[PDB]
Image (cartoon, rainbow over all chains, first blue to last red; front, side, top):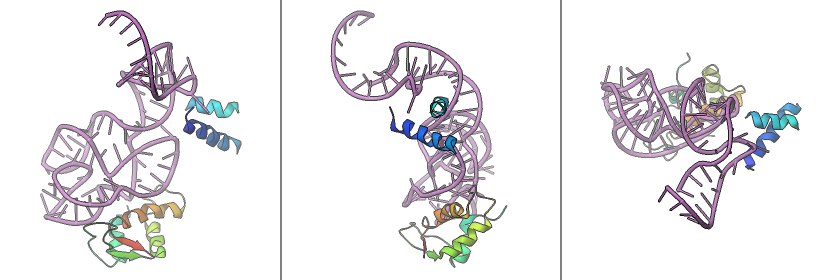
Length: 29
Length: 70
RNA sequence: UCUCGAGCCCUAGACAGCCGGGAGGUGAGCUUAGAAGCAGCUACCCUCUAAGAAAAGCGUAACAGCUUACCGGCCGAGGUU
């Protein structure tokens, strides 16, 4: 449950809002 | 293209050689404006987008030679 | 080779392998005719970024070149101490 993987998703979800697994993760959100 | 940093500093700095030990031995100083000009001479040699960042790169070789700022 | 225990990592993809990336300021400053990761001394900073040392090991007369770190992909289940 690394914190950096959590912070990453938030950073990705932040760009979409305006690793493949992490992208899919952000997208799924 | 444009000449290297190490030199562009030794010009407006008024000195030729650095210090045996950087940040420990301040050889010269540099007003913020002075660095605002150098950052302009190397607009192509740097990756940065804003002039702000371009400085950090330039302003990185200074304190590492004894080139304080004001 | 068998058996038992402890710590840590892992399907948000671990360990290994293979493929791709390993970038700019800048060949840091000093020393030096020259030294550019890698003779030595000192410092060891910031851009772009998913990464990428002021460079860990070879290599060079010095470059070059070959790789490590680091990141991404393929793969898919335990792995490591």
